[PDB]
Image (cartoon, rainbow over all chains, first blue to last red; front, top):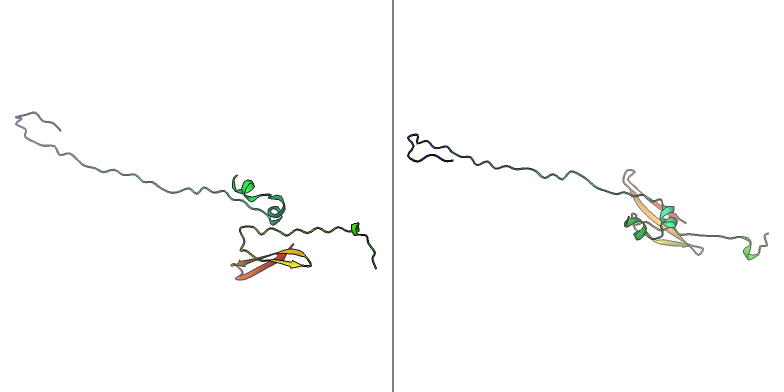
Length: 55
Length: 54
């Protein structure tokens, strides 16, 4: 604050120290699910890496 | 009795590929063909299920 010098009203105004805060929350679950019948895994799926995992 | 030339009848066999999501099981043999053996524990029924197929 400020006050004029040599003022008869010698009164002081106190400041305040307030600490704020927020919150980070972990609340979403991102997934990708696949199902393959054993016939598809045996015959149809040629290579598991380049045809299933990469996509 | 049956008298057949070689090319009369055709047989084809394929051993299923055990997927990565199953506990590894041995591969067996029957008359020259290979068979996939696969075990899985059923928690709901408190049992163990085995499958041997081709």
